[PDB]
Length: 291
Ligand SMILES: [Cl-]
Image: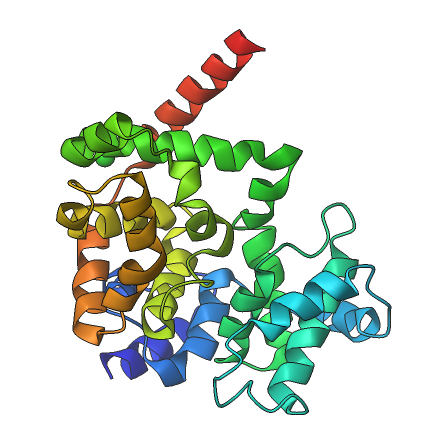
Protein backbone atom coordinates (compact mmCIF):
# COMPACT_ATOMS: atom_id res chain seq x y z
CA UNK A 1 0.00 0.00 0.00
CA UNK A 2 0.76 3.26 1.49
CA UNK A 3 2.09 0.34 3.73
CA UNK A 4 4.54 -0.83 1.12
CA UNK A 5 6.07 2.63 0.81
CA UNK A 6 6.12 2.95 4.58
CA UNK A 7 7.98 -0.33 5.09
CA UNK A 8 10.56 0.64 2.46
CA UNK A 9 11.08 3.88 4.32
CA UNK A 10 11.29 2.13 7.67
CA UNK A 11 13.91 -0.35 6.40
CA UNK A 12 16.26 2.59 5.67
CA UNK A 13 16.41 3.19 9.41
CA UNK A 14 14.94 0.35 11.54
CA UNK A 15 15.89 2.32 14.68
CA UNK A 16 13.27 4.99 14.14
CA UNK A 17 9.57 4.64 13.40
CA UNK A 18 8.45 6.70 10.39
CA UNK A 19 6.33 9.73 11.33
CA UNK A 20 3.15 8.47 9.67
CA UNK A 21 3.26 5.02 11.30
CA UNK A 22 0.99 5.69 14.27
CA UNK A 23 -1.77 7.01 11.93
CA UNK A 24 -1.50 4.03 9.61
CA UNK A 25 -1.55 1.56 12.53
CA UNK A 26 -4.76 3.19 13.81
CA UNK A 27 -6.51 2.02 10.66
CA UNK A 28 -5.32 -1.54 11.08
CA UNK A 29 -2.19 -3.37 9.83
CA UNK A 30 -2.76 -5.63 6.82
CA UNK A 31 -2.87 -9.30 7.73
CA UNK A 32 0.00 -10.27 5.50
CA UNK A 33 2.26 -7.48 6.87
CA UNK A 34 1.58 -8.08 10.59
CA UNK A 35 4.31 -10.63 11.06
CA UNK A 36 6.94 -8.12 10.00
CA UNK A 37 5.28 -5.02 11.40
CA UNK A 38 4.63 -6.47 14.83
CA UNK A 39 8.30 -7.46 15.12
CA UNK A 40 9.47 -4.03 14.07
CA UNK A 41 7.00 -2.30 16.50
CA UNK A 42 8.30 -4.45 19.34
CA UNK A 43 11.95 -3.65 18.39
CA UNK A 44 13.03 -7.16 17.47
CA UNK A 45 14.56 -7.65 14.08
CA UNK A 46 16.73 -10.65 13.76
CA UNK A 47 17.04 -10.90 17.65
CA UNK A 48 19.52 -13.68 17.41
CA UNK A 49 20.09 -14.15 21.20
CA UNK A 50 16.52 -14.92 22.14
CA UNK A 51 16.28 -17.33 19.14
CA UNK A 52 19.48 -19.07 20.33
CA UNK A 53 18.08 -19.38 23.86
CA UNK A 54 14.71 -20.61 22.47
CA UNK A 55 16.41 -23.49 20.68
CA UNK A 56 17.81 -24.66 24.03
CA UNK A 57 14.72 -23.89 26.03
CA UNK A 58 12.64 -26.26 23.88
CA UNK A 59 14.77 -29.17 25.02
CA UNK A 60 13.79 -28.60 28.63
CA UNK A 61 10.82 -29.95 30.61
CA UNK A 62 8.07 -27.57 31.78
CA UNK A 63 6.96 -27.69 35.40
CA UNK A 64 3.57 -26.40 34.11
CA UNK A 65 2.67 -29.09 31.58
CA UNK A 66 -0.85 -29.51 32.91
CA UNK A 67 -1.86 -25.87 32.92
CA UNK A 68 -0.35 -25.43 29.47
CA UNK A 69 -2.13 -28.44 27.98
CA UNK A 70 -5.47 -27.33 29.48
CA UNK A 71 -5.08 -23.82 28.06
CA UNK A 72 -3.97 -25.05 24.61
CA UNK A 73 -7.04 -27.35 24.37
CA UNK A 74 -9.24 -24.22 24.72
CA UNK A 75 -7.08 -22.04 22.41
CA UNK A 76 -8.86 -21.54 19.09
CA UNK A 77 -9.33 -25.35 18.75
CA UNK A 78 -11.67 -25.05 15.78
CA UNK A 79 -9.42 -22.73 13.84
CA UNK A 80 -8.01 -24.25 10.60
CA UNK A 81 -4.43 -23.71 11.68
CA UNK A 82 -4.87 -25.28 15.18
CA UNK A 83 -7.62 -27.96 14.68
CA UNK A 84 -5.24 -30.80 13.66
CA UNK A 85 -3.74 -31.94 17.02
CA UNK A 86 -0.66 -33.23 15.09
CA UNK A 87 -0.28 -30.10 12.99
CA UNK A 88 2.56 -27.73 13.02
CA UNK A 89 0.48 -24.98 14.65
CA UNK A 90 -0.37 -26.91 17.73
CA UNK A 91 3.22 -28.25 18.00
CA UNK A 92 4.66 -24.71 17.84
CA UNK A 93 2.10 -23.42 20.34
CA UNK A 94 3.12 -26.04 22.91
CA UNK A 95 6.81 -25.35 22.40
CA UNK A 96 6.41 -21.56 22.82
CA UNK A 97 4.32 -21.90 25.95
CA UNK A 98 6.70 -24.48 27.51
CA UNK A 99 9.73 -22.44 26.57
CA UNK A 100 8.23 -19.35 28.17
CA UNK A 101 7.58 -21.25 31.40
CA UNK A 102 11.26 -22.10 31.54
CA UNK A 103 12.50 -18.64 30.44
CA UNK A 104 10.60 -16.72 33.08
CA UNK A 105 11.81 -18.52 36.16
CA UNK A 106 10.27 -16.06 38.57
CA UNK A 107 6.64 -16.19 37.26
CA UNK A 108 6.38 -19.04 34.75
CA UNK A 109 3.61 -19.59 32.23
CA UNK A 110 0.64 -17.30 32.87
CA UNK A 111 -2.99 -18.41 32.54
CA UNK A 112 -4.24 -17.42 29.13
CA UNK A 113 -0.87 -16.83 27.60
CA UNK A 114 -1.55 -19.52 24.98
CA UNK A 115 -4.15 -17.29 23.34
CA UNK A 116 -1.64 -14.49 22.91
CA UNK A 117 1.02 -16.96 21.69
CA UNK A 118 -1.49 -18.28 19.14
CA UNK A 119 -2.27 -14.77 17.88
CA UNK A 120 1.43 -14.24 17.23
CA UNK A 121 1.87 -17.68 15.54
CA UNK A 122 -0.97 -16.78 13.21
CA UNK A 123 1.26 -14.04 11.74
CA UNK A 124 4.93 -15.05 12.13
CA UNK A 125 7.09 -18.12 12.52
CA UNK A 126 7.55 -19.95 15.80
CA UNK A 127 10.94 -18.58 16.82
CA UNK A 128 9.86 -14.96 16.14
CA UNK A 129 6.53 -15.49 17.94
CA UNK A 130 8.48 -16.58 21.08
CA UNK A 131 10.66 -13.38 20.80
CA UNK A 132 7.62 -11.12 20.50
CA UNK A 133 5.87 -12.91 23.34
CA UNK A 134 8.86 -12.26 25.59
CA UNK A 135 8.87 -8.57 24.62
CA UNK A 136 5.14 -8.25 25.39
CA UNK A 137 5.59 -9.96 28.80
CA UNK A 138 8.78 -8.19 29.81
CA UNK A 139 9.22 -4.92 27.81
CA UNK A 140 5.54 -3.94 27.47
CA UNK A 141 4.96 -5.21 31.00
CA UNK A 142 2.26 -7.82 30.87
CA UNK A 143 3.98 -10.06 33.39
CA UNK A 144 3.77 -7.30 35.98
CA UNK A 145 0.04 -7.81 36.32
CA UNK A 146 0.75 -11.38 37.71
CA UNK A 147 3.20 -10.34 40.50
CA UNK A 148 2.33 -9.83 44.10
CA UNK A 149 -1.06 -11.64 44.05
CA UNK A 150 -2.16 -9.42 41.14
CA UNK A 151 -1.58 -6.08 42.93
CA UNK A 152 -0.90 -4.21 39.62
CA UNK A 153 -4.09 -5.69 38.13
CA UNK A 154 -6.04 -4.31 41.13
CA UNK A 155 -4.44 -0.96 40.30
CA UNK A 156 -5.72 -1.17 36.74
CA UNK A 157 -9.23 -1.95 37.99
CA UNK A 158 -9.13 1.20 40.14
CA UNK A 159 -7.84 3.21 37.23
CA UNK A 160 -10.59 1.87 34.90
CA UNK A 161 -13.28 2.79 37.43
CA UNK A 162 -11.90 6.36 37.92
CA UNK A 163 -11.87 6.76 34.09
CA UNK A 164 -15.45 5.48 33.91
CA UNK A 165 -16.53 7.98 36.64
CA UNK A 166 -15.07 10.63 34.38
CA UNK A 167 -16.00 9.50 30.84
CA UNK A 168 -18.99 7.19 31.33
CA UNK A 169 -20.58 8.67 34.52
CA UNK A 170 -24.00 7.12 34.03
CA UNK A 171 -22.57 3.64 33.74
CA UNK A 172 -20.24 4.18 36.72
CA UNK A 173 -23.20 5.30 38.81
CA UNK A 174 -25.26 2.27 37.85
CA UNK A 175 -22.47 -0.13 38.59
CA UNK A 176 -22.14 1.51 42.01
CA UNK A 177 -25.89 1.11 42.55
CA UNK A 178 -25.74 -2.65 41.76
CA UNK A 179 -22.30 -3.17 43.42
CA UNK A 180 -20.63 -4.46 40.30
CA UNK A 181 -16.87 -3.93 40.44
CA UNK A 182 -14.44 -4.15 37.60
CA UNK A 183 -12.81 -7.33 38.88
CA UNK A 184 -16.02 -9.09 37.99
CA UNK A 185 -15.78 -8.25 34.29
CA UNK A 186 -12.44 -6.77 33.15
CA UNK A 187 -9.89 -9.28 34.40
CA UNK A 188 -9.39 -11.17 31.07
CA UNK A 189 -9.33 -7.90 29.14
CA UNK A 190 -6.16 -6.89 31.00
CA UNK A 191 -4.53 -10.22 31.72
CA UNK A 192 -4.94 -11.58 28.15
CA UNK A 193 -5.12 -8.30 26.22
CA UNK A 194 -8.62 -9.40 24.98
CA UNK A 195 -7.13 -12.51 23.24
CA UNK A 196 -9.08 -14.93 25.36
CA UNK A 197 -12.68 -13.86 24.62
CA UNK A 198 -12.90 -11.52 21.58
CA UNK A 199 -13.06 -12.36 17.89
CA UNK A 200 -9.67 -12.66 16.13
CA UNK A 201 -10.34 -9.86 13.63
CA UNK A 202 -10.79 -7.39 16.45
CA UNK A 203 -8.02 -8.92 18.59
CA UNK A 204 -5.44 -8.48 15.77
CA UNK A 205 -6.31 -4.77 15.57
CA UNK A 206 -5.89 -4.49 19.33
CA UNK A 207 -2.37 -6.02 19.14
CA UNK A 208 -1.52 -3.65 16.27
CA UNK A 209 -2.43 -0.68 18.57
CA UNK A 210 -0.89 -2.18 21.68
CA UNK A 211 2.49 -2.91 20.06
CA UNK A 212 2.58 0.63 18.60
CA UNK A 213 1.29 2.69 21.55
CA UNK A 214 1.83 0.50 24.58
CA UNK A 215 -0.10 -1.62 27.08
CA UNK A 216 -2.20 1.39 28.16
CA UNK A 217 -4.37 0.94 25.09
CA UNK A 218 -6.28 -1.74 27.04
CA UNK A 219 -7.88 1.22 28.87
CA UNK A 220 -8.89 2.84 25.61
CA UNK A 221 -10.46 -0.34 24.32
CA UNK A 222 -12.15 -1.02 27.69
CA UNK A 223 -13.72 2.47 27.67
CA UNK A 224 -14.75 2.11 24.05
CA UNK A 225 -16.45 -1.22 24.73
CA UNK A 226 -18.29 0.11 27.87
CA UNK A 227 -19.38 3.34 26.12
CA UNK A 228 -20.60 1.49 23.04
CA UNK A 229 -22.70 -1.02 24.99
CA UNK A 230 -23.63 1.15 27.98
CA UNK A 231 -27.35 1.27 27.05
CA UNK A 232 -27.44 -2.55 27.23
CA UNK A 233 -25.88 -2.32 30.73
CA UNK A 234 -27.51 0.71 32.39
CA UNK A 235 -30.88 -0.90 33.12
CA UNK A 236 -29.57 -4.44 33.89
CA UNK A 237 -29.30 -6.03 37.30
CA UNK A 238 -26.12 -7.75 38.52
CA UNK A 239 -26.88 -11.08 36.84
CA UNK A 240 -28.00 -9.33 33.68
CA UNK A 241 -24.80 -7.28 33.41
CA UNK A 242 -22.67 -10.44 33.79
CA UNK A 243 -24.62 -12.33 31.20
CA UNK A 244 -24.13 -9.41 28.74
CA UNK A 245 -20.41 -9.32 29.32
CA UNK A 246 -20.15 -13.15 28.94
CA UNK A 247 -22.29 -13.78 25.82
CA UNK A 248 -23.62 -10.70 23.98
CA UNK A 249 -20.59 -8.44 24.22
CA UNK A 250 -18.07 -10.57 22.29
CA UNK A 251 -20.82 -11.61 19.83
CA UNK A 252 -21.34 -7.98 18.76
CA UNK A 253 -17.75 -7.85 17.49
CA UNK A 254 -18.06 -10.78 15.14
CA UNK A 255 -19.10 -7.99 12.71
CA UNK A 256 -16.03 -6.33 11.09
CA UNK A 257 -17.89 -3.06 10.80
CA UNK A 258 -18.69 -3.07 14.55
CA UNK A 259 -15.07 -3.86 15.33
CA UNK A 260 -13.74 -1.07 13.10
CA UNK A 261 -16.03 1.54 14.70
CA UNK A 262 -14.99 0.28 18.09
CA UNK A 263 -11.25 0.67 17.48
CA UNK A 264 -11.86 4.14 16.01
CA UNK A 265 -13.71 5.14 19.23
CA UNK A 266 -11.01 3.58 21.39
CA UNK A 267 -8.36 5.66 19.64
CA UNK A 268 -10.55 8.75 19.96
CA UNK A 269 -11.17 7.99 23.71
CA UNK A 270 -7.31 7.88 24.15
CA UNK A 271 -6.17 8.44 27.84
CA UNK A 272 -2.94 10.34 28.69
CA UNK A 273 0.00 8.86 30.54
CA UNK A 274 -0.22 11.83 32.91
CA UNK A 275 -3.80 10.99 33.86
CA UNK A 276 -3.08 7.26 34.27
CA UNK A 277 -0.05 8.02 36.51
CA UNK A 278 -2.20 10.32 38.66
CA UNK A 279 -4.71 7.57 39.26
CA UNK A 280 -1.88 5.01 39.89
CA UNK A 281 -0.45 7.37 42.56
CA UNK A 282 -3.96 7.76 44.16
CA UNK A 283 -4.34 3.95 44.33
CA UNK A 284 -0.86 3.52 45.87
CA UNK A 285 -1.57 6.23 48.49
CA UNK A 286 -4.87 4.55 49.39
CA UNK A 287 -3.26 1.11 49.70
CA UNK A 288 -0.55 2.55 51.98
CA UNK A 289 -3.18 4.03 54.34
CA UNK A 290 -5.12 0.76 54.72
CA UNK A 291 -1.78 -1.10 55.12
CL1 LIG B 1 -6.91 12.41 29.11
